[PDB]
Image (tube, coloured by chain):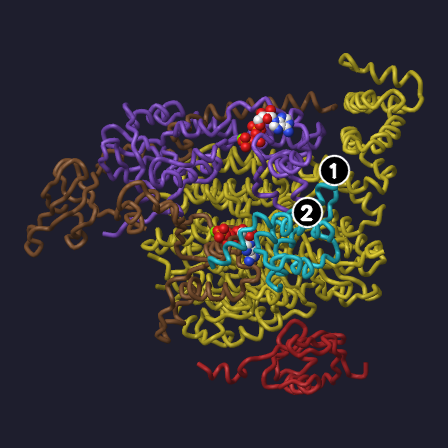
């Protein structure tokens, strides 16, 4: 006997998350309403028109068992009901993995073909068949209650106009958290990466949080707020674990 | 303009006051300009008397459009009315680049006869404004042999002219200059690529990669937790240090390694010595002679093809390669013959030289020539006369095709005869209806394959969707193999047609997935090859992930073809991620020698030339189509449709066809005296500059390196400073730099 | 603006064509982790669900009478139970050793496949899968530092032949120390980019764990 | 000094610097400075140029960047406390 | 003219000489005599060279006119490793 060898490089999932999937149409330039854009727009339409005719012809002569709604129905039959939720412990092979159910019992089950294999990572929540425990799906993890705490869902109502006298301070903070996103070309044409970090320091009440609130009001990026005292945890390693998770949500 | 305005907005304009048009507003003329094109199509031939005031407006609308930077709308006007000619008279110095850059981008989608016509007007503008280097680029795209001479000799600045020979030599088109032309010698020397070896060797000396590489350093078996193995490592050896001239495995006591191979393994192992001396015509010939006297049948014939590989891509004045191999094209042993024609095909690919062709033509008609020899002669003659529509080769290739038997055409080596005919008409277009009529008389199913293949090579790099429409219909009807052999060519056809512009190529990737889903085995075995052709030396993740999932497929050919496609997609890129995948695939396919041979073949290709070479058929900002490179690629991938019998069989020397497609991904900036001139340049991903006015950046995510740097696919280069004015805007290959008079004022 | 009316007409058709294509091909769900249908081998999956039985993960504890022709294996099936079982006939007796995880069926619990040792998912995530974008050319003023770093951590793996011939055992450890910002992690990022062997990044604060002996466990599994 | 000039060359490689940026002089203006400070000096030097709507970083911009990073930010410098540890 | 032909030869880049060098000789002489003098005229060793003229290898026995050479013909010099007899005798 010889150990199975994976064809996938590594054990981690694909970095890309939340893409356009197969709707990634080519980026047509220029955006101006001209004939070249019209020619490119027709060009994309032409291939789709070919695509529609080609796919229809195959499915027309495809067997009644092999149909888009029939195969989807067969997938549900293969998955079954209920759909147990487990934990991915190890990816032994491309189509084999070690999973553990909620009772703590591990199983050496087979990852079925319809499973999104690039969402598979150790520790992820996997969906298993009730009977044969085979991997039949991956549970899109719900937003952690820890995520909701950091995220400021609604931007604060404090603007830069509500700040008086911190003209230089606004200008310095804008250039590291606002300008790099609004006008990233300024940094690229200069060849400089934007100032990495920023710290606001001074006497109490001087407007440190207020400028951050103004930053959160006029930001297109996700804003995560954590007070430093919230990093003191009641258990060993949890504090380091929390700092690790905070920047994981940021990623 | 408030309502529909059908034959009204122009009418009161036409009949009313004839004052200056812009006095009524920019938005008014824009609607007015949109009208004059709409009514132009409606007007028939009998309505020629109705365009007298219609013409007057466009002589004023175009000058109005260029005044307010609304230049791209000006091209949109006279392209619709098919009157692009009058643009050049009103082109100013402040917008000549913007007008050219726009309509040249439309040449990838507008069909004939507006295809050439739009280029001709752009050609006229560049000729008018004395922008010779970009005028020559347009001429080659139109494959106007006559116009190339006129563009070349019109210029008087000799410094400007040597730059063209670099561009002309890179495209592989030869010009026979007159001795009366000043600086005749170096002009030929530059375009004949005789100095390419020294320039290539001097480059890598600056990159300090002269150290030879063993296949073990590529394999990295020490991190891993036979005749095929030895023959596989021969390719991996030659590919890694191709055109480098030094090898720790063949030059150093090559007899033990060369004889470690067996049967046809020694054929490719011996020929691999000519690939490490690629472009080294003088020095490379000095090394193959030791194996040229070998008593074994394969070694000499392998050394025969090695000379052709050595002289491939280099055109010297006085011809060695024909001499060493002419005496063996009728040699009684087919293997001795076999190493000859494929040697001549690579040695003179894209030459259209009647000397080699007439010497090679009777070989295919010989009684002693087997079908294996018959195929390579069509392949080779196709490379010499690629895209030339040579009348002589068409007659004999057709003659051979119908003279063969019904059972003879069943052999997969017979598939090569159509490619030779297809190669001759590479990119020619509709010049095949006479040829396609001749293919009617030949028997089935070979006729369907031959009809599909030659039609595909006709429209190579054209993007003609109507032709791709036919190709998908051929793929539509499935057959429950023998009758569906032609289906693989149609899939390779879609890539060969859509490889023109980016929009079509990416739009073809999704259609490749559907053939990869609804397809049948013989239809699904070729779509990995289409991915390789459509994106060779372009290791984009979408194709690689698509190929990665399908490397371990149930169908052996799909597994074999997909892995090879990964290597060709990353050919010469030295991609760290791809090498990791190929190393992992080696572990998975350890117990499958056939799959592992494909994995080993891919590992050699991704480290081709130590990352200093590319197989992409496109250069000049991915706008110029190289006839020789497509011939080299097409030879390999069309041979991969029968990967069981040809590549994995006794005929793996066909993998040396991509030698014709080997070029260095080069940026070497030369002084006016052709000496090296290292300066700071900015290398980064190209950005489309069509549309937006002003000065938009054409590179993003760029970095600053010295000049002798290897440019990856899709990476443009701009000079960081203004110390030197490039002769040509396109900063690829060898570039001549001139001191800027305004600089250091 | 003259093409504005026609551009939206073809843009909407493309969107309508795109949605129509998704109707036949199928681009949906993605919340139960369903792969695109291009990778769906339903015929094979049905065969796997019958031909390939599921195997429960168990650890061998003792082999009884290994010398004889009736070797009996005591297995610990996680939290389920402990069973004295015999080996399956499609695996070799020499392939199962005491203390090694095995895969057992649900009916007679006979060992069907040996399994890799259990590793903490956190420890598994410690190995670098995407190399950094930093090379040694991005480290300046550390010429002597890098050569010492490379000849211990890079040279032995790249060219091991130069050390075995001379009977040399190269050092197996390097400590990089200096004030913050001096390039300690920068050089290690260059090492991971250039290295071909497995690279595992372990931050010391990651080894601090809530429970007693857990931090030492992760070092053992690492 | 040689190492600091080398780090300056590394981080100012992709910058849009002027003709005669005296990188040896800039390396001399920060005697005991980590490579992290040198990178920030390069970033702030181009950051002053962005401030002035200028596409090329002059030598004065680097001189101001050295003052802001090496001199003004010397209160928070971790170097003096950590050389005793190393 | 007067029984002497203009033979332009090519030299390898290792011998850093003028690659556009001119060789003058009779036509009644043979290939064996030719190979000797090309070595002398540009400082080379005759035992380790092949000559090719009119895109066909210089057959040493056959005389020039019966070889097929003509006026303003172009030639080259190929450096050799191991002699033609030595290479055959090697294995
Ligand atoms: N410069 C200012 N302009 C306008 N309002 C200000 C300014 N400085 C402080 N304030 C007001 O003071 C309030 C409280 O100050 P803030 O929360 O910003 O303090 P801080 O600077 O973060 O200090 P700390 O957290 O140390 O107490 C703000 O909500 C804001 O309305
Ligand atoms: N020798 C160097 N050459 C070039 N850049 C350097 C050099 N040393 C540091 N840098 C730059 O400074 C940054 C400092 O980060 P780095 O990871 O090197 O710090 P460190 O020495 O590990 O610090 P700490 O002890 O706080 O962890 C690097 O990311 C790099 O951009
Ligand atoms: Mg506060
Ligand atoms: Mg660190």
Task: Mark yes or no: residue B576 visible.
Answer: no
State the residue position of label 1.
Answer: B103
**Figure check: B176 above or below C209:** below
* Chain the render paints purple: A
Q: Nearer the viewer, residue B224 or B720?
A: B720
Residue at (76% x, 74% y) in the render: E72
When the figure is inspected, residue A22 is found, relative to residue B175, above or below; the finding is above
What hue does chain D carry in this figure?
cyan
Secondary structure of residue under mark 2:
helix
| Count of number-bearing discs | 2
Q: Residues within 10 Å of mark 2 (few under 14, many from 20)?
A: many
**Residue D46, label in figure:** 2
User: In the rendered image, what is the letter of the chain coloured red?
Assistant: E
Chain shown in brown: C
- Give residue E78's quadrant in the image: bottom right
Residue D42: give x, y in percent of width and height. 64, 51
Q: Residue at x 53, y 26 (%)?
A: C18
Please rate how many residues cluster around mark 1, counting C-alpha atoms within 10 Å: few if below 14, some from 14 to 19, many from 20: many
Query: What is the display colour for chain B?
Result: yellow
């Amino acid at each position: 006997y010889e150990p199975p060898v994976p064809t996938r490089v590594g054990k981690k999932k694909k970095k890309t998350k939340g893409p356009d999937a197969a709707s990634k149409l080519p980026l047509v330039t220029p955006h101006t309403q001209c004939r070249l854009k019209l020619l490119k727009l027709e060009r994309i339409k032409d291939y789709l028109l070919m695509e529609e005719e080609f796919i229809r012809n195959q499915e027309q002569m495809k067997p009644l068992e092999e149909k888009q709604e029939e195969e989807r129905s067969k997938v549900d039959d293969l998955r079954g009901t209920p759909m147990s939720v487990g934990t991915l412990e190890e990816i032994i092979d491309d189509n084999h993995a070690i999973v553990s159910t909620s009772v703590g019992s591990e199983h050496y089950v087979s990852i079925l073909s319809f499973v999104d294999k690039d969402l598979l990572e150790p520790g992820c929540s996997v969906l298993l068949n009730h009977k044969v425990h085979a991997v039949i799906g991956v549970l899109m993890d719900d937003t952690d209650p820890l995520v909701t705490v950091m995220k400021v869902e609604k931007a604060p109502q404090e603007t830069y106009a509500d700040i008086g006298g911190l003209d230089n301070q606004i200008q310095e903070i804008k250039e590291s958290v606002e300008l790099p996103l609004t006008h990233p070309e300024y940094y690229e044409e200069m060849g400089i990466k934007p100032p990495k970090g920023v710290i606001l320091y001074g006497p109490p009440g001087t407007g440190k949080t207020l400028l951050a609130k103004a930053v959160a009001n006029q930001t297109s990026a996700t804003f995560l707020r954590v007070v430093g005292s919230e990093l003191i945890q009641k258990y060993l390693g949890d504090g380091p674990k929390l700092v690790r998770e905070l920047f994981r949500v940021a990623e | 303009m408030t309502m529909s305005g059908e034959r009204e907005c122009l009418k009161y304009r036409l009949v009313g006051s004839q004052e200056e048009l812009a006095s009524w507003g920019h938005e008014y003329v824009r609607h007015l300009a949109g009208e004059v094109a709409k009514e132009w199509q409606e007007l028939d031939d009998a309505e020629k008397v109705q365009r007298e005031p219609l013409l007057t407006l466009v002589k004023e609308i175009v000058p109005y459009n260029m005044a307010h930077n609304a230049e791209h709308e000006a091209c949109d006007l006279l392209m619709e009315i098919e009157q692009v000619d009058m643009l050049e008279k009103d082109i100013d110095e402040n917008a000549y680049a913007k007008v050219c850059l726009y309509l040249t981008s439309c040449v990838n989608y507008v069909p004939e006869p507006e295809n050439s016509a739009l280029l001709r007007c752009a050609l006229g503008v560049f000729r008018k404004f004395s922008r010779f280097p970009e005028a020559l680029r347009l001429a080659l795209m139109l494959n106007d042999m006559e116009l190339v001479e006129d563009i070349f000799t019109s210029c008087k600045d000799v410094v400007v002219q040597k730059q063209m020979a670099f561009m002309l030599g890179r495209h592989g088109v030869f010009l026979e200059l007159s001795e009366d032309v000043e600086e005749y010698e170096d002009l030929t020397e530059i375009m004949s690529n005789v100095q390419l070896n020294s320039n290539f060797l001097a480059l890598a000396r600056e990159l300090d990669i002269m150290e030879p590489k063993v296949p073990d350093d590529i394999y990295k078996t020490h991190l891993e937790n036979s005749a095929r193995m030895n023959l596989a490592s021969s390719f991996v050896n030659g590919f890694v240090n191709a055109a480098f001239g030094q090898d720790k495995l063949l030059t150093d006591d090559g007899n033990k390694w060369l004889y470690k191979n067996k049967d046809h393994g020694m054929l490719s192992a011996a020929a691999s010595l000519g690939m490490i001396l690629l472009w080294d015509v003088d020095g490379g010939l000095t090394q193959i002679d030791k194996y040229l006297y070998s008593s074994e049948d394969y070694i000499k014939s392998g050394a025969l093809l090695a000379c052709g590989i050595v002289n491939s891509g280099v055109r010297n004045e006085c011809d060695p390669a024909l001499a060493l191999l002419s005496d063996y094209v009728l040699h009684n042993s087919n293997t001795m013959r076999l190493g000859s024609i494929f040697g001549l095909g690579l040695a003179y690919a894209g030459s259209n030289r009647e000397d080699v062709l007439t010497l090679l033509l009777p070989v295919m008609g010989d009684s002693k020539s087997s079908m294996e020899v018959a195929g390579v002669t069509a392949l080779a003659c196709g490379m010499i006369a690629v895209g030339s529509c040579n009348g002589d080769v068409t007659s004999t290739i057709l003659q051979t095709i119908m003279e063969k038997s019904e059972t003879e055409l069943k052999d997969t080596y017979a598939r090569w005869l159509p490619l030779g005919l297809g190669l001759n008409h590479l990119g020619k277009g509709e010049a095949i209806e006479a040829i396609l009529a001749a293919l009617e008389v030949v028997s089935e199913p070979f006729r369907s394959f031959a009809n599909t293949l030659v039609d595909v090579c006709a429209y190579a790099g054209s993007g003609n969707v109507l032709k791709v429409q036919q190709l998908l219909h051929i793929c539509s009807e499935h057959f429950d193999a023998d009758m569906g052999a032609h289906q693989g060519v149609a899939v390779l056809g879609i890539a060969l047609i859509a490889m023109g512009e980016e929009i079509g190529a990416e739009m073809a990737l999704r259609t490749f997935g559907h053939l990869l889903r609804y397809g049948e085995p013989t239809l699904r075995r070729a779509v990995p090859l289409a991915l390789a052709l459509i994106s060779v030396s372009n290791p984009r993740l979408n194709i690689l992930d698509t190929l990665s999932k399908f490397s371990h497929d149930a169908d052996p050919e799909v597994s074999y073809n997909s892995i090879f496609a990964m290597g060709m997609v990353g050919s010469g890129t030295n991609n760290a991620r791809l090498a990791a995948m190929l190393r992992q695939l080696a572990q998975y396919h350890a117990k499958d020698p056939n799959n592992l041979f494909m994995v080993r073949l891919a590992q050699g290709l991704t480290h081709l030339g130590k990352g200093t070479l590319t197989l992409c058929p496109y250069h000049s900002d991915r706008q110029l189509m190289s006839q020789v490179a497509v011939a080299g690629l097409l030879t390999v991938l069309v041979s991969f449709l029968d990967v069981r019998n040809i590549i994995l069989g006794k005929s793996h020397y066909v993998l040396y066809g991509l030698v014709a497609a080997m070029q260095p991904r080069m940026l070497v900036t030369f002084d006016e005296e052709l000496r090296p001139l290292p300066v700071s340049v900015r290398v980064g991903q190209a950005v489309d500059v069509v549309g937006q006015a002003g000065k938009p950046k054409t590179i993003t995510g760029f970095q600053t390196h010295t000049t002798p740097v290897l440019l990856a696919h899709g990476e443009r280069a701009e000079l960081a400073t203004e110390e030197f004015l490039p002769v040509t805007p396109i900063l690829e290959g060898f570039v001549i730099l001139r001191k800027n008079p305004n600089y250091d004022l | 603006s003259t093409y504005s009316r026609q551009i939206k007409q073809v843009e909407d058709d493309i969107q309508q064509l795109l949605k129509k294509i998704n109707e036949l091909t199928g681009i949906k769900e993605s919340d139960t982790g369903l792969a695109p249908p291009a990778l769906w081998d339903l015929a094979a999956d049905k065969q796997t669900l019958q031909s390939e039985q599921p195997l429960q993960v168990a650890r061998c504890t003792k082999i009884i009478n290994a010398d004889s022709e009736d070797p009996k294996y005591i297995i610990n099936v996680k939290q389920f139970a402990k069973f004295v079982v015999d080996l399956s006939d499609q695996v070799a007796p020499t392939d199962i050793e005491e203390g090694m995880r095995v895969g057992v069926d649900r009916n007679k619990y006979q060992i069907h496949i040996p399994l890799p040792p259990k590793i903490d998912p956190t420890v598994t995530m410690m190995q670098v899968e995407e190399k950094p974008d930093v090379t040694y050319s991005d480290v300046g003023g550390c010429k002597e530092q890098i050569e010492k770093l490379r000849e211990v951590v890079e040279t032995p793996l790249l060219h091991p032949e130069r050390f075995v011939n001379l009977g040399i055992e190269p050092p197996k450890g390097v400590l990089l120390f200096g004030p913050p910002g001096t390039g300690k992690t920068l050089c290690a990022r260059a090492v991971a980019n250039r290295t071909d062997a497995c690279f595992i990044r372990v931050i010391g604060s990651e080894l601090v764990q809530k429970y007693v002996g857990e931090g030492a466990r992760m070092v053992r599994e690492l | 000094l040689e190492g600091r000039t080398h780090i300056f060359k590394i981080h100012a490689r992709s910058m849009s610097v002027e003709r005669d940026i005296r990188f040896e002089l800039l390396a001399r203006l920060c005697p005991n400075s980590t490579g992290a400070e040198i990178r920030s000096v390069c970033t702030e030097a181009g950051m002053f140029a962005i401030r002035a709507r200028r596409k090329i970083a002059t030598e004065k911009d680097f001189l101001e960047a050295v003052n802001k990073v090496i001199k003004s930010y010397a209160k928070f410098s971790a170097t003096p406390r950590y050389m005793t540890y190393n | 003219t007067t029984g002497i032909a203009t033979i332009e030869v090519f030299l390898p880049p290792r011998l850093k000489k003028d690659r556009k060098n001119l060789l003058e000789t009779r036509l009644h002489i043979t290939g064996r005599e030719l190979r000797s003098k090309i070595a002398e005229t540009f400082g080379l060793q005759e035992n380790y060279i092949k000559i090719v003229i009119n895109k066909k290898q210089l057959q040493l026995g056959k005389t020039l006119e019966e070889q097929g050479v003509a006026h303003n013909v172009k030639a080259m010099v190929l450096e050799l490793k191991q002699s033609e007899e030595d290479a055959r005798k090697n294995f």
